[PDB]
Image (cartoon, rainbow, N blue to C red; front, side):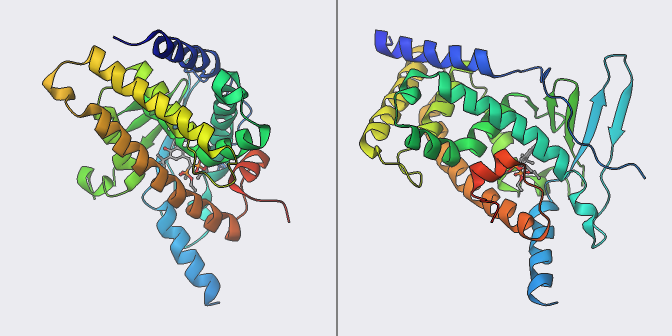
Length: 279
Ligand SMILES: CCOP(=O)(OCC)C(=Cc1cc(C(C)(C)C)c(O)c(C(C)(C)C)c1)P(=O)(OCC)OCC
């Protein structure tokens, strides 16, 4: 029951996703790994500890030869050990950000925007699109993001309910429970990417019209393909999660800048996307 334009729109988005989402992470290489073996500033450190303590994961690397490396992070002992996985995660996030920049650039609707708006939209949405792609490799039964030969497992710290307190973790579990199709994930990416109210966007009206068309396409897709009672209000649930994801983006951006202030680690691409000039 989709129009021809809506069908073409999903086709273009799915093409872009297929071309730019390395779901096996085969080309993620040469990344860093954790090493083997005042008053104003003290308040900053206390906040940064809170920014990180509920986001801890262990890391597993499965070798092509069948070997397995496993890393368990240190406990918070008041020192720099809370940062041990940040270079690695900066490298993974940077890899993902390159993929979502590539995703945007192959979409006609994005390519046709002024280059300054393209940059403003990617700066605005990079974390959101990255997390949406990460949700598709999230295993909610094991609390693990399965990234090809790499796995990131939430540290069983509190318990299951106490871990749902962290908004980005609650988001991953809640989104996984909706059991979305690839097409619904890629339309979520489009709706996030074409957000007319990101800082710096000049073509507000064009971007707003584009976003509405992606949202209408998603609404129509769901109506045409999901008649089951479980999917009543699914479109509205998804849109509400996209609004929540924008809020989480702002909050994790604040965490990033707080950490960067006392412990610089952002890669050059992260600096460009999240507003760090190099002073
Ligand atoms: C705003 C920029 O954030 P960011 O890309 O930065 C890279 C360091 C970032 C990325 C990130 C976040 C999560 C949570 C939040 C779902 C736990 C992950 O599970 C993962 C992996 C790689 C393990 C799948 C990466 P951040 O939210 O979490 C990493 C600690 O970083 C905010 C400081």
